[PDB]
Amino acid sequence: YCCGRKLEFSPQTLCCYGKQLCTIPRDATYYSYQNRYHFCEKCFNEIQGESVSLTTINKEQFSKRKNDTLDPELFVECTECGRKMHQICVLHHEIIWPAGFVCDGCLKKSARTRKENKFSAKRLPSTRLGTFLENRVNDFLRRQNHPESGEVTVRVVHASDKTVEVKPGMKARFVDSGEMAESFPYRTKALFAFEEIDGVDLCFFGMHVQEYGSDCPPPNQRRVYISYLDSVHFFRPKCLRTAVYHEILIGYLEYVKKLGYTTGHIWACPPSEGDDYIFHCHPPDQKIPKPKRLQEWFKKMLDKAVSERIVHDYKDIFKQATEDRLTSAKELPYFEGDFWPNVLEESIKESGGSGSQKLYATMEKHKEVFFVIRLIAGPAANSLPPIVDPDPLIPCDLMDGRDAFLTLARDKHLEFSSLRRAQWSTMCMLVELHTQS
Ligand SMILES: COc1ccc(C2(C(=O)N3CCOC[C@H](Cc4cccc5[nH]ncc45)C3)CCCC2)cc1
Ligand SMILES: [Zn+2]
Ligand SMILES: [Zn+2]
Ligand SMILES: [Zn+2]
Image (cartoon, rainbow, N blue to C red):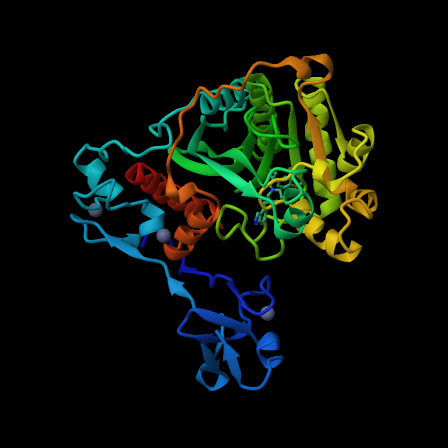
């Protein structure tokens, strides 16, 4: 055996299908039907009668289970030794090495090494935005001159044109009356950061963004929104991990500012317990920050951006609307999946059809969570040329949003819960991106 350890995958968390946001953690009790519809023990017993609509399926046909199934880790056999070894430990992928697995001992005994690993992070197609970010990170790393650090690769893996649609409450008030556009076009992008750790790629950062160009009507035009952020905390060295995140995030703001976007938007929202934003099965000791801590962290990152003469200034949404002399909810930027489109639906219902009644009160209530970042200020923003993106569209269904990658990771036991598993998951992720390309 490679190690002395007996290893297996932890059970993943499933949905309860009752409260539409309820989740079933590890070792919990739940009910299943056809392994498709799972129900919380509390939510299932708080059900009308026996018949449950799914077609009505009776509660008699449901399975009472505990979320404690442990799938053992897989082994691979050396085609010369016969030695059985963990697939994750030796990082053997059948697509990269279709000739069969040969252990390190056999390779050295015959004075050879594995064939070069195609489908690497470096060999992913590059972009102007990706090169811009990885130059910034690697230049910073050489300045710090830590011998433990490795080369960082940043690649944009998806780009497509989409639209966000105004929800029925806001649509009935402002869209049907002609006061607001019914949809806002934007380009979505997914990019990841990789670090070479002992000769092996490790994906440690991911990000999805929404970019609304000069074609977009107000109030969305020339604005960028960060849909989701995620990380795996195994960047080496640890003492430089936060700074690298700052380099990527500030670099993105610097890049879109150069392109002509005037404002960036960040919703400082930590994930719920047991929830994964981009990377499936985070390490158990990678703690989720509390909201106050996360807000201060973004402040520090933005403060550095201001000092670097990249970000002009930043304010919370409540302060921004006051300076913008906002009066109606139709003047607030409308982003896909954002907090505010959902809340404006609730605000109109409670107000009897008003888009202004509790607008400032709601913004003040949640002001510390929403950051409005001004990249271009004053007279310069009034007369800018059209935004032209030098990078082409990158069709990649696996990265059209965060759902496909999470599903693939769930379906293939691709965990990021440890360095070895995250390296195996990185290798599998890279192979998928190269074949789907
Ligand atoms: C102040 O401490 C931090 C500040 C920022 C981050 C970043 C990040 O990754 N965030 C910020 C939101 O909370 C942490 C999420 C990571 C995470 C941790 C544990 C379980 C999870 N499930 N899903 C996501 C997830 C995603 C790092 C780079 C960008 C900001 C991480 C920790
Ligand atoms: Zn092992
Ligand atoms: Zn539930
Ligand atoms: Zn061998």
